[PDB]
Image (cartoon, rainbow, N blue to C red; front, side, top):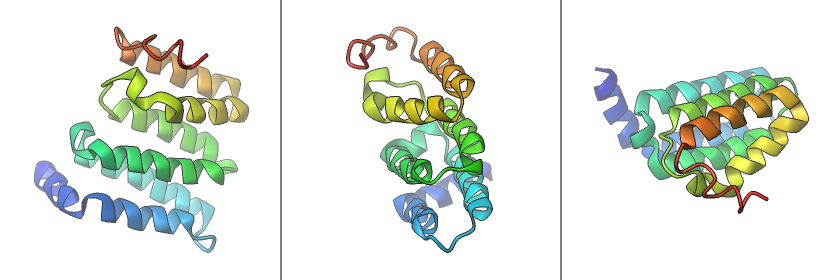
Length: 139
């Protein structure tokens, strides 16, 4: 079952994500392979579902930040993947994403003006009433 697969993914929990993060951390893993792993991480996050990812999704965002640290060609795909991960993530609280969403947006804006803008517009729409709670915080 995809839900059964999600339950198996839930049993792996942070450690499977940590193993992916460790592979992302390693210099040896190929950037295209890392991009495939990032696509896999987005697929795994989808398989878990937003509620299942929970704190691990925030850990995944930290892993995404490690992915952000070396981006190159992968980053334009990664920025779409990060936007997809945000889209996969429950809107929850805009304030709860806080700086990490802003930090991702700033990296995305450097990679392309449009990629950050598309993510920001999606983020604002998803945040809804929550959106602008952190707008003052993200001066």
